[PDB]
Picture 1 (cartoon, rainbow, N blue to C red):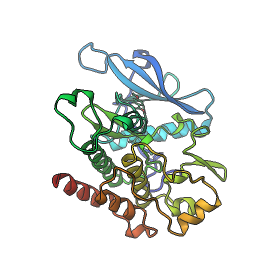
Picture 2: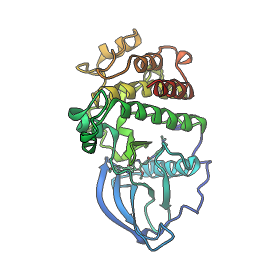
Picture 3: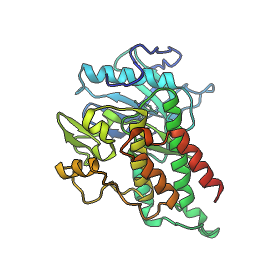
Picture 4: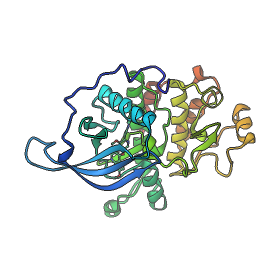
Length: 306
Ligand SMILES: COc1ccc2c(Oc3cnc(CC(=O)Nc4cc(C)cc(CN(C)C)c4)c(OC)c3)ccnc2c1
């Protein structure tokens, strides 16, 4: 199955989510893949008062086949199932009748974290920010720790609901107001065929540099494989949006080195204690890797200490 613990087809879909598609006015595309897209839209009547609201709508393109159509439905059943959580992109509604299925979520105004990190890289301040220059919205080490904590909190939640992400990366984390991170999954709304972070492994285009050895060599995805990905996310975060294993292509030598125990060194801005988390996430033995709840407790202490 394309889901390890839960079966989304057996999961129900509450019609409390059902939203009239005529009440959706579409805007610009926030992201698009071969078979799907995420578009910005204005939803009318989503609030008790006549007030309009900005939402993000995931949908398929006419290029999509039955397997993608089924994927979008199962994705909807899972989002319905998870419900409200601060560190997860929240579902607002859906359109199942009247045409193609539309998945309506909240709009995260700052977009994906990867691009945010990249545009903030050159103005990053490791130490404390001056009171005068606070308006400039400088990225600090405090924000990075807050983001690493929130993503673990979100992942801990997902894990308690027996959900495996299978693509935990900075590109699949959105940033909203108040420096709040929200785990998402662009999936079909990402052009993986042209994204250099995805690699041809057999007949698939997989994010190999974020995958645990067991996921690469056995296509087994567990709670422990998501912890590995998180460790790579931590590297991207404290590297301020750098691509993992810089200068190393995904070749025979790459696979051999990961199997043999090669692991990235600490990014330039990673506190020593955060690198310790990354090293444990990358343990060759999945049973020796921390759980997301362990990670939460670890980061929580690091935060209090500062
Ligand atoms: C300003 O720029 C932007 C740019 C993009 C935006 C945005 O993009 C989206 C990303 N993804 C989805 C679907 C999704 O998140 N699925 C999903 C999420 C979780 C927590 C769990 C699972 C289960 N899987 C197996 C792990 C699936 C969207 O649906 C409409 C939109 C959302 C909000 N605001 C956006 C603002």
